[PDB]
Length: 288
Ligand SMILES: CCC(C)(C)c1ccc(OC[C@H](O)CN2C[C@@H]3C[C@H](C2)c2cccc(=O)n2C3)c(C(C)(C)CC)c1
Ligand SMILES: [Zn+2]
Image (tube, rainbow, N blue to C red; front, side):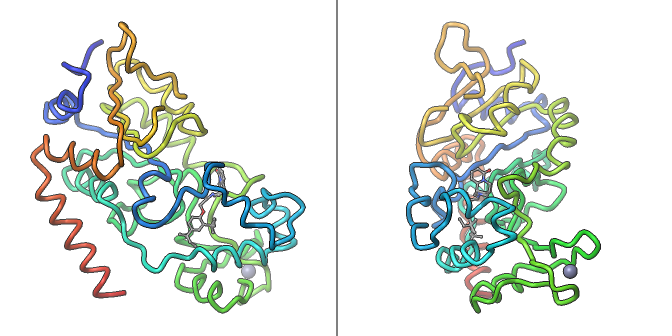
């Protein structure tokens, strides 16, 4: 089935404004947070895994490996102190997703990011699937305790260079991120099944799809679901933008903010979006 009239941003805009497009899923990666001064720590190109020499790890990946972390948590928290941002300011792209929520178009945002910016932008727990977890909350690692700690507590521990320990049972306190050797959250697998039935549009932003878990996700949405990619680079996932058989996939190449602004324009949301970014940034400035 053919749902987009044309395989262009204009066509996607037009589809979004039609009665057909009720439920949008966003899939978002590190590219939506780069313009917030969170660089893409994941992808190898960034070279994060070269600044780790001073932590004398057995191998660079050890800094994110759960068993290593439990024995030697100090490098992870030192790194966190090193790279902790001055402010947490969500990007235009984040606020575009806020618009989708408030217009009742957002079914779900699946995010690879742990930076909490979606939450700060006003996306709620129901709206979000944090595929790699989050720094927003932390928990004592003991299964009989699991004392919860807010980011404010974790930040203080990070800045004081005191290893987070549970006030109750003395166990290590770990940010709710998915370390190497830990499994994806159950939430991820459960929401996927149900969501990928009801979805009318996939908005894929700041991820190359060459990389799990979005590579798989994309390939098992219904065949007729239109998919728009907004990314600096070209897309895995089994997308088809270019062939004579292309029917549903659209690529916008450039920065995520600029792509979102362009899409907002066509929807007639540009002013609303620019105003929201300005207002929410000012609010953050006032309370920071
Ligand atoms: C404190 C500043 C803050 C919250 C703003 C921030 C933000 C991002 C941060 O890191 C982003 C990483 O890309 C998150 N990844 C989470 C885990 C382990 C690593 C790293 C990884 C690599 C490749 C695939 C993959 O799935 N995963 C999952 C980090 C740190 C602390 C973890 C220091 C690097 C902190
Ligand atoms: Zn505890």
